[PDB]
Amino acid sequence: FPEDSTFASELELYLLRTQDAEQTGMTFVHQVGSTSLPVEARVAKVDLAKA
Amino acid sequence: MDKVKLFQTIGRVEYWERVPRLHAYGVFALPFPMDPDVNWAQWFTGPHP
Protein backbone atom coordinates (compact mmCIF):
# COMPACT_ATOMS: atom_id res chain seq x y z
CA PHE A 1 0.00 0.00 0.00
CA PRO A 2 2.03 3.00 -1.18
CA GLU A 3 0.87 5.99 0.82
CA ASP A 4 -1.10 8.95 -0.50
CA SER A 5 -2.35 12.24 0.88
CA THR A 6 -5.47 14.34 0.46
CA PHE A 7 -7.14 17.35 2.05
CA ALA A 8 -10.73 16.09 2.19
CA SER A 9 -12.46 13.62 4.47
CA GLU A 10 -14.63 11.17 2.55
CA LEU A 11 -13.56 9.35 -0.61
CA GLU A 12 -16.03 8.63 -3.40
CA LEU A 13 -15.13 6.45 -6.36
CA TYR A 14 -17.65 6.70 -9.18
CA LEU A 15 -17.22 3.96 -11.76
CA LEU A 16 -18.99 4.21 -15.13
CA ARG A 17 -19.37 0.80 -16.70
CA THR A 18 -19.92 0.59 -20.45
CA GLN A 19 -21.02 -2.38 -22.54
CA ASP A 20 -20.68 -1.18 -26.10
CA ALA A 21 -22.51 -3.00 -28.88
CA GLU A 22 -20.16 -5.64 -30.21
CA GLN A 23 -19.47 -5.39 -33.93
CA THR A 24 -20.87 -8.78 -34.91
CA GLY A 25 -22.73 -10.15 -37.87
CA MET A 26 -21.88 -11.27 -41.37
CA THR A 27 -22.95 -9.50 -44.53
CA PHE A 28 -26.08 -11.03 -46.01
CA VAL A 29 -25.71 -13.21 -49.09
CA HIS A 30 -27.63 -12.21 -52.21
CA GLN A 31 -27.57 -12.60 -55.98
CA VAL A 32 -26.55 -9.86 -58.42
CA GLY A 33 -29.59 -7.93 -59.58
CA SER A 34 -31.55 -7.64 -56.36
CA THR A 35 -32.78 -5.10 -53.85
CA SER A 36 -30.81 -5.28 -50.60
CA LEU A 37 -32.20 -6.26 -47.19
CA PRO A 38 -31.49 -4.38 -43.95
CA VAL A 39 -29.53 -5.29 -40.87
CA GLU A 40 -30.71 -6.10 -37.36
CA ALA A 41 -30.78 -3.78 -34.36
CA ARG A 42 -28.18 -4.02 -31.59
CA VAL A 43 -28.00 -2.85 -27.99
CA ALA A 44 -25.49 -0.90 -25.90
CA LYS A 45 -25.73 -0.49 -22.13
CA VAL A 46 -24.37 1.90 -19.50
CA ASP A 47 -24.31 1.17 -15.77
CA LEU A 48 -22.69 3.17 -12.97
CA ALA A 49 -21.24 2.46 -9.54
CA LYS A 50 -20.75 4.34 -6.26
CA ALA A 51 -18.21 3.49 -3.57
CA MET B 1 -10.18 -32.08 -103.69
CA ASP B 2 -6.86 -33.21 -102.28
CA LYS B 3 -4.25 -30.44 -102.34
CA VAL B 4 -6.48 -27.37 -102.07
CA LYS B 5 -9.55 -27.26 -99.83
CA LEU B 6 -12.01 -24.47 -100.55
CA PHE B 7 -13.79 -22.23 -98.05
CA GLN B 8 -15.81 -23.93 -95.34
CA THR B 9 -17.52 -22.43 -92.30
CA ILE B 10 -16.36 -23.27 -88.79
CA GLY B 11 -18.48 -21.61 -86.11
CA ARG B 12 -21.37 -19.19 -85.75
CA VAL B 13 -22.66 -16.82 -83.06
CA GLU B 14 -26.30 -15.72 -82.93
CA TYR B 15 -26.26 -12.86 -80.42
CA TRP B 16 -29.39 -11.15 -79.12
CA GLU B 17 -30.55 -8.15 -77.14
CA ARG B 18 -32.24 -8.12 -73.72
CA VAL B 19 -35.84 -7.97 -72.47
CA PRO B 20 -36.68 -4.36 -71.56
CA ARG B 21 -38.97 -2.93 -68.89
CA LEU B 22 -40.41 0.49 -68.04
CA HIS B 23 -38.07 3.17 -66.71
CA ALA B 24 -40.70 4.98 -64.66
CA TYR B 25 -42.25 1.85 -63.16
CA GLY B 26 -39.39 0.79 -60.92
CA VAL B 27 -38.05 -2.71 -60.52
CA PHE B 28 -38.18 -4.58 -57.22
CA ALA B 29 -36.32 -7.89 -57.20
CA LEU B 30 -35.28 -10.52 -54.64
CA PRO B 31 -33.11 -13.65 -54.98
CA PHE B 32 -34.65 -17.11 -54.57
CA PRO B 33 -33.19 -20.62 -54.82
CA MET B 34 -34.03 -23.09 -57.56
CA ASP B 35 -36.14 -26.21 -57.36
CA PRO B 36 -33.55 -28.83 -58.37
CA ASP B 37 -35.83 -31.47 -59.92
CA VAL B 38 -36.88 -29.23 -62.84
CA ASN B 39 -34.68 -29.34 -65.95
CA TRP B 40 -33.54 -25.74 -65.61
CA ALA B 41 -31.14 -26.08 -68.54
CA GLN B 42 -34.13 -26.60 -70.86
CA TRP B 43 -35.41 -23.12 -70.07
CA PHE B 44 -32.11 -21.42 -70.89
CA THR B 45 -31.25 -22.90 -74.29
CA GLY B 46 -32.26 -20.34 -76.89
CA PRO B 47 -30.22 -17.19 -77.48
CA HIS B 48 -33.31 -15.17 -78.37
CA PRO B 49 -34.52 -13.42 -75.22
Image: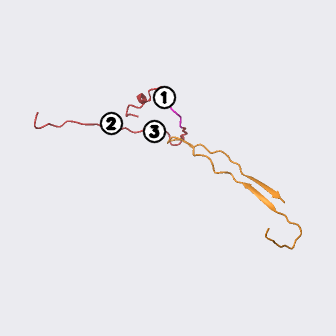
Chain colours: A orange, B red
- Circle 2 sits on which residue? B14
Q: Residue at image x 63%, y 51%?
A: A23
Establish if A45 lies above or below B41.
below
The percent coordinates of residue B2 (x first, y second) are 10, 34
- Same chain assignment for discs 1 and 3: yes
Identify the chain of the residue marked 2, using the numbered disc in the image: B
Residue B30 picture quarter: top right
Q: Give whichever of discs 2 and 1 has the lower sequence position.
A: 2
Nearer-the-camera pick, B22 or B49? B49
In magenta, the rendered stretch is B31-36
The percent coordinates of residue B38 (x first, y second) are 47, 26
Cβ–Cβ under 8 Å for marks 2 and 1? no
Tag 2 secondary structure: loop
* Inter-mark Cα distance, 2 to 1: 29 Å
Q: Residue at image x 42%, y 30%?
A: B41
Check the picture and name the quadrant holding the C terminus of chain B. top left
- Circle 3 sits on which residue? B20
- Identify the main secondary structure in magenta: loop
* Inter-mark Cα distance, 1 to 3: 28 Å
- Decide whether residue A16 is among the magenta residues: no
Tag 1 secondary structure: loop
* Inter-mark Cα distance, 3 to 2: 19 Å
- Same chain assignment for discs 2 and 1: yes
